[PDB]
Image (cartoon, coloured by chain):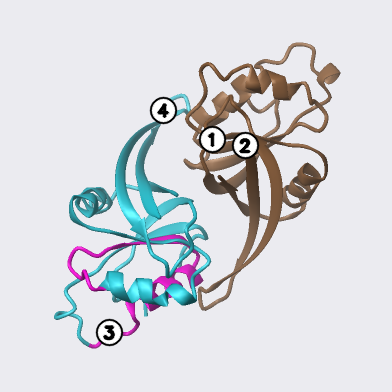
Chain colours: A brown, B cyan
Amino acid sequence: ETAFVEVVLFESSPSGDYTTHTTGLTGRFSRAGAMLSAEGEIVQMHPLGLCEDLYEYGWVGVVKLEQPELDPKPCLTVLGKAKRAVQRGATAVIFDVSENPEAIDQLNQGSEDPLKRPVVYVKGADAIKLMNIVNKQKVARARIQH
Amino acid sequence: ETAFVEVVLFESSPSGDYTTHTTGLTGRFSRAGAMLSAEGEIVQMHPLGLCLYEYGWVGVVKLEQPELDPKPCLTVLGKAKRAVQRGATAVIFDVSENPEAIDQLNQGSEDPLKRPVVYVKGADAIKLMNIVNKQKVARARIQH
């Protein structure tokens, strides 16, 4: 099932009223994860960063995968990476699998013991759109639907 | 459209790992707001108080007898937009003591809010409020 992702940028005024800019994206839910919506602030984690460096409960991990031959022995599989994130309070995880499309099977290999939070992958222009904000922008919220 | 609400309590671990306790309850979407899911930290707002906050919160607002606030600053529908104006990702109203608020909300039906407005009552607001009241930090997940 397809996942609609929204990345929201926001400025307060001095008065306290907020002003937001939404960008829409389409990815897919992994069967490694629940098929629920989730929303929460974005944390960019390196894949080397998933093996008390704590973050507030309910963040949305955005993770750009590496060429797979640039990682002979991963500390964890991409499955275990998402599972780690969750243990550390990730409300959801989003992988950019543009460099590592084998990863989709690896995720969907874990459908026997799925996580109660959503694991979403994105490729192509929808990943491009995502990472371009996550990199440039200060600080963002993500909403994942349906 | 009925709304399923999970309230989440959580504790980090010596190892930086979280442990959660989730309490579920059922409420309803108002046609005055969008029928979408939403998640966010809970901020308890006092009704007088919607006439300072991190973007993406979920407002929990307990209404009171309309006999006791008889010069209201905004309609209850107004209070919700105000909350959204102030970064609320969704608003939850406990309408146990002002049941005619259902009516006001679902009357804004024709011109709605981008975010969800949900009303709860009875044993479901009792659960929600019995957590929110005991000043912990909590997360709210609202599900369509």
Kindly check if marks 3 and 4 are in contact, taking CB atoms under 8 A apart as contact: no
The span from disc 3 to disc 1 (Cα, nearest Å) is 42 Å
At mark 4, the secondary structure is: loop
Viewer-side residue, A66 vs A23 = A23
Kindly check if marks 2 and 1 are in contact, taking CB atoms under 8 A apart as contact: yes
In this figure, which residue is indicated by the disc labeled 3? B72
The span from disc 3 to disc 4 (Cα, nearest Å) is 45 Å
- Residue A36, x across and y down, in percent: 51, 39
At mark 1, the secondary structure is: loop
Residue B85: in magenta span = yes
The span from disc 2 to disc 1 (Cα, nearest Å) is 8 Å
The span from disc 4 to disc 1 (Cα, nearest Å) is 27 Å
Dot 1 crowding, Cα within 10 Å, few <14, some 14–19, many 20+ = many
Kindly check if marks 4 and 2 are in contact, taking CB atoms under 8 A apart as contact: no
In this figure, which residue is indicated by the disc labeled 4? B13
Dot 4 crowding, Cα within 10 Å, few <14, some 14–19, many 20+ = few
